Structures are given as C-alpha cells and as structure tokens.
Image (tube, coloured by chain):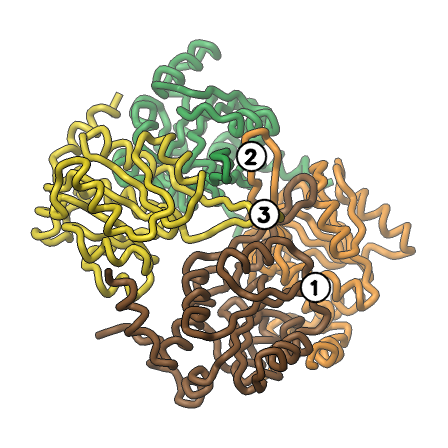
Chain colours: A green, B yellow, C orange, D brown
Amino acid sequence: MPYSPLQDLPADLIDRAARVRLACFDVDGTLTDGRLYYDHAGNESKAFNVLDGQGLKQLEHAGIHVALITARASLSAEKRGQDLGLHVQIGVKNKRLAVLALCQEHGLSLDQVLFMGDDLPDLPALLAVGLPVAPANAHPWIAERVQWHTRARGGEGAAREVCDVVLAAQGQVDSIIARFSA
Amino acid sequence: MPYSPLQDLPADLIDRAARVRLACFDVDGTLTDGRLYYDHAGNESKAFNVLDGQGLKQLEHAGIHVALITARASLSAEKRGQDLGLHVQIGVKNKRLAVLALCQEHGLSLDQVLFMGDDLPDLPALLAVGLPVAPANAHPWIAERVQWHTRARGGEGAAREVCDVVLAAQGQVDSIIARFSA
Amino acid sequence: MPYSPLQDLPADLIDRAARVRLACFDVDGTLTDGRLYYDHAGNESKAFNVLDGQGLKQLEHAGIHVALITARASLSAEKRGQDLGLHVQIGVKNKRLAVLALCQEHGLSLDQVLFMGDDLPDLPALLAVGLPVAPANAHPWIAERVQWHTRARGGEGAAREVCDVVLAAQGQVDSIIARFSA
Amino acid sequence: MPYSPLQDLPADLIDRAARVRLACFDVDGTLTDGRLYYDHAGNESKAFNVLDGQGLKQLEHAGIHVALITARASLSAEKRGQDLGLHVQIGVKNKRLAVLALCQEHGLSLDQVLFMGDDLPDLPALLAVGLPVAPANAHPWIAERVQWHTRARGGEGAAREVCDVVLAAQGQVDSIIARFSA
C-alpha cells in the first residue's frame, strides 16, 4: 500500500496545500532542532537536514517559490539558501510584514502562502497565512494556535514532511519519481 | 483546553515562582544536553537552544534578572549571555557564594532566587535558593534533592519550560501572547 | 543464542549478499544521520560513525571492494574514504552511471553489486543493482522501492549492519571474531 | 527511596566493582555516541559528555586510576584526558597489551581492572579484565561476550553509570555528596 502524505489529512488542508504558491520557513526549530552550536569565540553553527533540503528543491522544481525567514542576522541561513537555490530574508523584525512583502513581489494573496514556524516570533505570520504549519517540537503556544502539526521534529524531516504534502496535493509526486528512476 | 505551564504544578511552587526576582542557570546539562564537542586542538563547542533563548529574553523583558553560572572558563557562555543580554559569571569555584554575591548586588533574599542545575557542582546553590529546579536529564543525586523537575531535557527546552512557569506565575502570559499575535 | 546478522533474513537476500564483490554507499543519510552542520561562513561538516568505519574496513579486509558515492563535491567524504582505505567518487550527476563505471573497472556484473542509499538521487542505482539496501531512516519513496531495510538508522550503525550481513553470508565471521579475541 | 547504582546488580559484579583500582575506557562509542564530525578539510571532532566527565574525576578523586585507550591517533582524546586529569594511551595496536602494561606500572592484577568498550578492537581487553562492561549501544558481538551492560548509551551517560556503580561499591557516595553540599 503506497505511502501518501495525504492520507489521514483533512480535505480542507489538502485543498489549501493544493493552492500554495509561496512556502516560507522559519529557520531555528523548524529546519533545525533548535540547537545553536557556539564555539570558543562565540561563532555559531546550526544543523540542517538533507531530507529537508531535498524537499525544498522539489518545491522550487515544482514552481513553488521558497523563502527562509529568520530574525537572526546569520550568514549560515544565507549560505544554506544559496546551496538549495531559495530566497532568504534575514534580520526580520516582523515576519508577517516580510511575508506580506513577498506576496506583492510575486503577485499573490495570503491565502496562497504556507508558513512553517515553531515559536513566538513566527506567530504573526502563522496567524495571517492561508496554510500555517508547525513541527512536532513546536512551543505549545504555537502548537495550540495552528492545526497542522507534522509528525516529525524540526531538523529531523519536519520540513520534508510538509514539502511531501504540498507536492502530493499538487499532483507532483509521480513525475518526481519518474525523473529520478533513471 | 489552553496550555498552562502552571497546571499539574503544586500551589507552593507556583507561589515561589511568583516571587522570583533573580533566575540563575547552570550552563552544561541545563542550557545544553551535556555535550562538549572537542575539536582536534582541544577547542570546545556547546549547543544552546533557541526556545531557551526566547524564554530568557522574556524573563529579562519582564524585569527579572537573569544570570548564567558556570565553573568552566569558557568564552562560549559569555558570548551566549551577550547575545541574549544577560549577566554571566564564569569560572566559579562555589556556586552558592556566586549566587549569594548576586543577591547582595540586587538587594535580594535567597527566597527570591531561582536556580536551575543538573549535577554536583550546582548542589550548594540548589540547596540554598528559594526555588531550585532540575531538568529531566539531571543526575539522580540532584533530581533526588530537588522537587521541581522539568518534563523537558537540558538543551531541549528545559529552561524555556522554567521561564514559562515563572512568567505564568507572574501574570505575564496574556501580554506575551498579545505582543506576538500580529 | 548467538547473534547472527542472517537470522530473520530471507534466503534470497542472503544468497545475493554472498555474491557481493562491490559495495557502494551513499554518504548523507546512509553513513550520516542526514545532518549538515553549517558554520557562519557556510562551511559544512557531517558526522560519520565508528561502527560503520569498522564494518567498512572489514569488507575491504575480506577482499570486497568498497566505494562511497556522493553528488556533493565535499572534501569531507574524500578525507573519510582515505582514513578507511576505500574508493570515493564525488560530485556524481548520476549514480547508476557511476556504479556502472565501477563494474567495468573491476570486471563485475550489476548482480554482484550492493548499493545503500536513503533518498531520490540514489534511486537510479538502487533499482539497477543486485542488492539494494536502505537504512531505517530512509525516505518512504525509497523504502517502498527496496526490500532490505536495516533495523538501524543512518549514522547510527546502519552501514555496519549491512557489512555484518555480507561478511556473515560470505563465511567471514568466525575468523573476524578469532582475530579480535586476544 | 534513594537511587542506588547497586540495586538490581548481582552480588558477583558488585564484588568485582569493589576491588577496581584501574578503570580503562574506550573513546569512540563508549565516551562518545560513535560519531565523528568531519569538517571540510577532513579535520575531526567528537562529542564527550559532562556527566561522564564528572564521573571520571570522581573515580580519580576516589583514588582509582583512570585511563583512556584508543587505537586512533587523536589529539582530541589527549586534550580530553588533560581537562579531566586522566592518563591517555593513543594509537594502541593491542588494547590487552596496553592494559597489561598499565597493570605492571601500578602494581596491579588484571582482576583489579575494569574495561569499558563497544566494538571489536576492545575485545582482547574485555576478555582479559576482571570487570568488562559495555554500553547499551555496543556492537552485538561485544554485547554477547560481556555480562554487564549499562542502561545508558555511549556519550549519553553510560560511563557515568559505570562510575556510579564503582563508587557505590567502594562506599564512596555519601562522602562525595557531603563534599558538594556546601
């Protein structure tokens, strides 16, 4: 019986995922397990996940715009966006306003936007977009306020889990597989 | 049913948390999962957690003084304190005395102090403060000697879990949520 | 009751493992838990596993050729191959073609090849070799398309688990144990 | 009911732990979760654990000699030994012979030695010492051949778990606690 990201998901959600044209992702706690590795000189590192990376490229490959949105002013996140070919917006005071800006740039509504975050700074956006989603490790204040929770944890495939849903809802999977079968 | 850091907590604890003016935290095993990454030249790194970071800022924002206290002489911990805007005391032979020094600096009693630690060097402080706490990963010798244990593990939101309680006990939640809702 | 990598495995698989002369391994998600540590300048690190290392040497010691195959252009993977004494092929657009090249270099058929991978870029190879395998953390699209799944996760002994099977199927165990018993 | 490392342990083991004068530890997979972090230039790091560190010092503080024994030629392990004040022997071809050498240096028998390891290179020693022990993540070939398994995993307190047993068997705990209570 074939894996389908869509079974056990409600019709309403699948319908929103089908119209997603812009997918935005918090960095820490969402593409990351929330950890910041500090070295002896205070320099910082984060761990991203390759399944998440593969998922994000596939969204881009399926004509969906992908954006990373972080309040931190980190070159890490920028370098990560470059490696996968995604937009990045760094040092953002308000994530809603950032998202709203990206809607105007691509000629989109908020109802065509997906946002994935894990904590308070993501909340303005989570409450404004057509399709908010939170990883399993999300702070309860965010979890409580978003219906769609991934089974997986941030930095352990939660973002891939989202990508798979969106791609499945947009009829993209069969062709993804066919491209990689030879 | 709204998430409340305070349900399933005894009245006595809530009442102590309500009077906390100074919150002190061990570094390793408390804001960290206990791990030290050693590089080929013996240089060390640690992992902090962004939920913990968000929690600590919120304590500071609510007018509660925050301090990190470590026996290790690490620039990591100092850099981390700077990034969040908190006091740091490094290389402490005795944590009780350090805490006691901080009480005098801010004109406080030990009854108005919270301390969170995971192992033996924290014990002198844990036994002296008004509100000791330990994360779930705490050594049993410490666990046994402190009533309040967080559900979460050090470096996986245990400190945020503490911050949430204190903030909740001090009536700070409703406004935290309002600030972030748009 | 002696541990045997071969119990609970079907005869057919054991028989294929017995004829393996070339063992190829994806890097990320297969010898790694899928994580990429990004530093402030975009420099990357990965974590390998020493049990996996011990397994790979033992394959080489038993006269089986070992190869690592990655699409990424990383010096990490090369350095890792050097440390264990195995062939490496980096930056591969198509893994099938790479494998096929290695068959010709060693005068082998695809039926004599094992390939272990976790995600889409491995699929062309997984579908072409005599003995595909996937770790437990493998993406479901890959899992679904390969019968042999290791109990262990990538970067947590999954590759050793494979090595053990192959070595067991090729009668190599008794002597491995004897070499190390004093 | 006070935590006792000794309950649920057989009398025979407790008796051997009571006479331990030399405690030797594999590095990788034993003080580490088996992971090797490779950076872009092939430089390696490992993660040690602070609970393990606290345990090792306490063994030293209780007059037990502690030694780290690795086949790898890593400055990491040396730097780690220095930080905790323990002997280190690096690049060891045969661990039994290394241990045997340390017995003669300290005027001890093999029956007064504890060895903790996780994989084949440790086996010669595990089979020669009075008290072998293996972490929960140990390779089955080693697990099968050693009776004492820690509940915890390497790099997640397995070595502390051992230290606690030995210290408890040697009547050391009460005084350890008393030293840290003020």
Q: In the image, which disc is placed on residue D91? A: 1
Residue A6 at least partly seen: no
Q: Residue at x 58, y 63 (%)?
A: D27
What residue is shown with label 2?
C39
State the image coordinates of residue C18 (x, y, percent, origin top left). Answer: 77, 69
The reply to whether callout 1 and callout 3 are in contact (CB within 8 Å) is no
How far apart are labels 2 and 1 at the CA level?
30 Å
Residue B100 position (above or below residue A53): below
Nearest to the observer: residue C133 or residue C72: C72
Frontmost residue, B133 versus C162: B133
Q: Residue furthest bottom?
A: D12
Label 1 residue SS: loop
Q: Which label is found at residue B177?
A: none
Estimate the x, y position of residue C40 in percent, counting from the top left.
54, 30
What's the chain of the residue with tag 1?
D
Q: Up-down: is D90 above or below A140?
A: below
Question: Which residue does the image show at 11% across and 54% down from the upper left?
Answer: B10
Q: Is residue B38 left or right of residue D72?
A: left
Q: Chain of mark 3?
A: B
Can you give x and y, in whole percent of width and height, for residue B53 in the image?
A: 34, 36
Amino acid bearing label 1: Gly
Label 2 vs label 3, nearer the camera: 3
Give the labeled residue for mark 3.
B39
Q: Quadrant of residue C23?
A: bottom right
Q: CA distance from mark 1 to mark 3?
A: 18 Å
Q: CA distance from mark 2 to mark 3?
A: 14 Å
The answer to which quarter of the image holds residue B52 is top left
